[PDB]
Length: 213
Length: 223
Ligand SMILES: Cc1ncc(COP(=O)(O)O)c(CN[C@H](C)C(=O)O)c1O
Image (cartoon, rainbow over all chains, first blue to last red; front, side):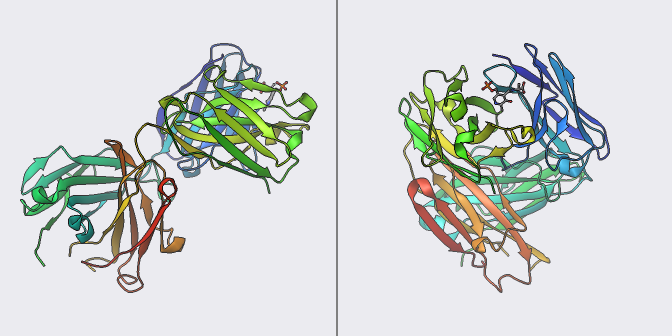
């Protein structure tokens, strides 16, 4: 019943920076295993038997430790290394995995590409009105969205969704959906999607004017 | 090529039972141990247990959180691994993976190295419901790149699969995680393509919802 605690639980590494992930046990283990899991994929064996690198695993990677304290280290951080890492012990049954370490890769600040869409004719025929907004490919993660109907701020009825760091360009994407009744939607004229990001002093905004045609 | 494929996952009512499967190939099944591992959405991996190979009498070992409720078995005929789950609870909602465990050799670098894609199990009393698919076309060629989208709302349970142009369009695609609200799931998917190709070629998102045996296509007409 060995529990494995990893620290840190979340971290950002600059390119080239050295990285160390620690895994501590409630009891001694003869070896420690590590797994790297990237978003939307299955875990992959990374280090086995404490320090042996698995197939396709770069040399900048290494593992060490014994007893109840083990670690995984990346000598020089690379974009390809961004992922969640997990330690594992099979020294005593039942086997167990660590709490995990979500490792993101720091990159050049990127302003979000904001796209707003008015409710489709289809949904409107159904009696519902969902206004959607995409805040694609930005960095850092910290972004704040605000909905403004005819100048006022809207809070309720706003469902947000955030992606994890993308492997293609190391950015983050967010989707914000505002659902309203056909009635409330037609009671107003201007819909805006306001996003505050460290890339700009003033909010990045997109809007559209409900039109009859 | 080693392949592991889970299934049996889907919506299941609290307190009931669900049996998961894992078809395999590319190696002599009986010579290997097999493990089951689960990961609840946004959480850590959890080892559920394993079953041994012939040489070791196909014995089983179990995690403490499931001893008694879950049983692991294997049909050595058809080379299939199984996981029987009884008295299911919400905490059991997760993605389950089968993994080739240790084998009768010293190919250590290969232990716990092969995992299936995983199957999603959802434990809830909420009823199934097909998704309504809505296109997302801009309001007003403003730029060199135009982003399009598809709204998939009010379905249950997960998952759903979104693709663009039968998959011929994988680049520039963004599919945000689903968000649950009042026993209903909603998700969106954006695609970015050059202004040139659209509206000139035709962009379509294909959505499939196995649970409801729903599958629909939605062209993206301008507006
Ligand atoms: C994948 C795997 N399966 C099964 C076992 C034990 O097999 P059995 O319970 O039949 O003897 C081990 C040993 N753990 C090693 C020693 C370790 O990492 O400490 C293992 O690594």
